[PDB]
Length: 136
Length: 136
Length: 168
Image 1 (cartoon, rainbow over the protein chains, first blue to last red):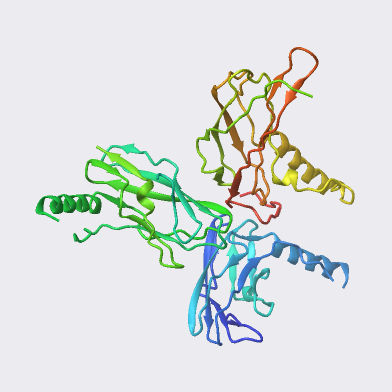
Image 2 (image 1 turned 90 degrees about the vertical axis):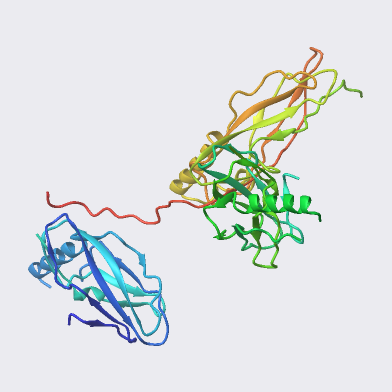
């Protein structure tokens, strides 16, 4: 579960420190490791979207879902948005040094929003499931 | 004479301030204008040669020539040696911001050694003819 | 019909140029000097006017405003107006030249807000000699071109808002 794989590919993603706790408002860093062994390099780009995902359910469940999506959207901000991971040559590894800062205290277990787009087949793998950020 | 063009090509070179006077020891900056209008971008690379040119003349003239070559060789140094001027697209211009520092007091009129190599046809044009550095 | 003697301007030199070529770092504002001389030996000009007009003001068809919304119309036309007025400008120009006088005047090229197709500049001047106090001024034209190239520098390609929720 913590180790997240990519569909229709062989690449692999893993946070070196998947569990981190830090005071709110202090920028922190996460080292995202990429393992590539398929055939060829890639140009995958990582980005965090701070937009409320539209909701599709009773009013209680509907508002629970909206609160969850709001906290996901405007809780954490990635200070290297639309980053271009340069090259990941075959049978080699690489570290994407992501930088964040939290603004809304909470427990962002398996944080969504952080999703990495592969610019070879338009993959939208949810790489952010291997994170357990806890900002006070 | 001060304005120098390139043989077997249309690119043209000119220093903004070809007449510069600075105290010896202090590093100075010389702004080289490139004109490109021929067909296509160039990948020219500029360097300063700090080796004594081998001599080919009586002893008098031969030692005069050797002293001149030594003064050219170990007088000035380019602090951006082997600078790859990135691109000069056609019908445009570019400023190669060369940076120097002198170590021997003298008048280096039409200084040699500063020669720019073109990595398309191996042109070894003498771009330094439009420089008149004087340093005390 | 026979007109009196007319003058001429030569463009003796420009200070920081090489055959009217320059580079700009897309946000920095520079300036330089223009030197001209009246060739005529008998009478000189009593009227100068500078009207720069670059490529983009030259390379927009007369009907651009037909089918566009008000907001983009305002944005583009504000850019055009600023480029017409607050762009490359003259400071401390002369008002009377003398025969065979090499006069020099300054020119400030300010491009803090120009688009990424500003590759061209066609400063044209119309000096003239007043007639013999009869009814008119005899104007002329001179259309010196400049080929300035604009590099690229810091640019913002995206935005967000994300309002705050909790004090720190």
